[PDB]
Length: 103
Image 1 (cartoon, one colour):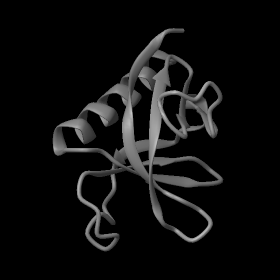
Image 2 (image 1 turned 90 degrees about the vertical axis):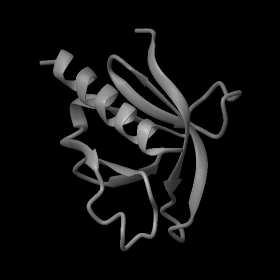
Image 3 (image 1 turned 120 degrees about the vertical axis):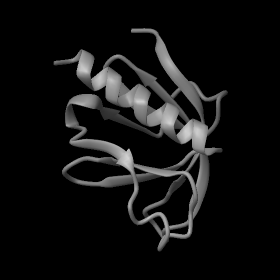
């Protein structure tokens, strides 16, 4: 249950749809995010079993955000901007591989 991937990404907030830098952490069962790398408790945990898709966001142009992927769950789609194209692909590949490993 160790960490597979961790790092900062900038995600869209629900209250007013602003974008905020948060620390993301993926392990074999969950992806969660934290206020920063120092925090002990996450702001939200998303069980990978509840992830229907993880993919490049096709609305990246309209949302005016480069390097944007999304995590689709029934109740909410999360919009997550990586720091580079390379990190966007790294995050998508890591989350998708962890979901595969759950099969």
